Image (spheres, each protein chain N blue to C red):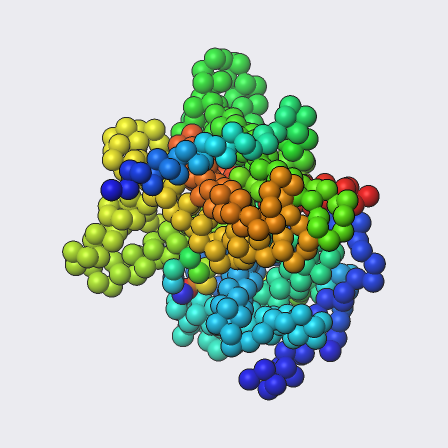
Length: 456
Length: 61
Length: 32
Length: 10
C-alpha cells in the first residue's frame, strides 16, 4: 500500500518549503498572483467542446466549488476538497497515519496530491463521457483525450496553487481563496458590468451603478430613472447592493464577537494571555456543509425525477420545472427569491428558515466534534501546554470549556444561518451563502494580518 | 418534550452573547476597512480579468 | 523528487494558459 | 458524484 504508492507519490511536483518566513505584504502579492491565475483560467474555455447546452445538475455546487462551466476550471476546487475529506476519513479510520515526522507528513502530502489527481482524472472522464461537451462518439478519441488532458493539467495547476498558498507563500488555502474570489467577482460584476441587454426599452446596462449613471444621463434625469435603477426586476438592483453592503456590515459585526477567556500558564510562569472563543466558532464550515448537502440533495432529486418520474417518493423528494424546485423537500429547502414568494407561501418561508437555522447549528456542532475543536479537544491543548484559566482550577478547565464552546458553536450556527436567511430575503447580491463565505474568508485574512502584526 | 432543552439553549446563548466581547466603534471600522480592501482586491481583479477576456474569448472562439 | 518555487509555478500556469490559447487559435485557423 | 455534504461532481 504505502510502500508501493510512495514511488507513485514522489512523481508529482511539490512546492519548495520557503527558506525564510514570508512577510505579509509579499504574501498578499503571491495570493493576488495565485487568484489572478485562477481567474484567468476560469475565463478560458476548453478546446474541443461542441455544445455547452446540457443539464448541468451541479449548478448549485458552483459558489462553494469555485467552478465555472465549460472553462479550464470546470471542476473548480472539487479535487482539493475531495482529496482532503478522503485523507481525513482515511486518517480517522486508521488505514494510514499522518504522523509527526517530516517524512511522514511529506508522504501524506504526496499521497494527498496523488489522490486529488486521481479524482481529477475521474471527474474529467465522467464529464467527457456522460454527454457534456458534446457527444463523446462525435468528438472522437482525440478530442475527448485532449479535453481530459486539459482538465487534468488544470487540476494539477489548482493543486499546485493551493500548495503554493499552504506552504507559506499565500494567505491561506486554495479552497477559501478561490471561493471568496468567485463570490467577490460575481458581486463586482453585478455592480459594474458593461454588458447590455435590450428588451424593447433601449440599451440597459447589466451592472447596477453603470445602469444608474446611464439612466440618469439619458432619461432626462427623471425621478423615474432613480426608481427603476433602485427597483429594477430584470437586472441587478441598487437596493440589492445596499442590502449586500448591509449584510456585509452585519456579518462583520457578528464575526467580531468573541468570548475572551483569561488564561495563564502553569508551566512558564508569567504568560498571561487570552483565549478567544469566537461566536462564529466554526467560521464558514456550516455554510459549506449546508450548501453541499442541499445541492447534493438537489442533484439526487434531479437524477431520480429524470429517470424514475411519476413515483410518489420521487415527487415528494422534489418537483422540478435550466431547472428550479417547485415542490417537495427540494422546494422547502430552497430560498424564497422574492418578497412576493414569501407572501404567497408563508409556510415555505418558515420551513426554509427553520431548516437553515437547524442545519447550520447541527453542522457546527458536528464539525466541532469532528475537526478536533471540541471542548475536550481544547482542554487537551490546555493540559499539554501548562495553560489554565485564570480564575478557575486546573481540574475544572474542561467544564468551563464544556459550558462555552458547545453553546458558542450552536449559536454561531444559528447566527450564521439567520444571516444567510436575511441576506436571501433582502435580495442581496452574492446571496447569503456567498456573502457569508466571502466575509468569513476575508476575516481569516485580516486575522492572519493582525496575528503577524502582533508577532512584530 | 423538548421545550426545556430549547429554553436551556436559549438561556445559554443569551448568557454567552452578553459575556462576549462585541466590536467597538474602532474595531468595527478596522474590520470593515480590511473586508472592503480584500473585497475590492479580489472582486476588481476578477472583474478586470473577465472584462479583458470577453474580447479574447470572442477572438479565439 | 522535484521541488519548484512560486515563480516556476507561475511560469507553468502561464505556459498552460498560452498552450490552451494556441490550441484555440490553431483550431480556428485550421477550420477556417 | 452526489453523496451527503461531500462536493465531488458528477
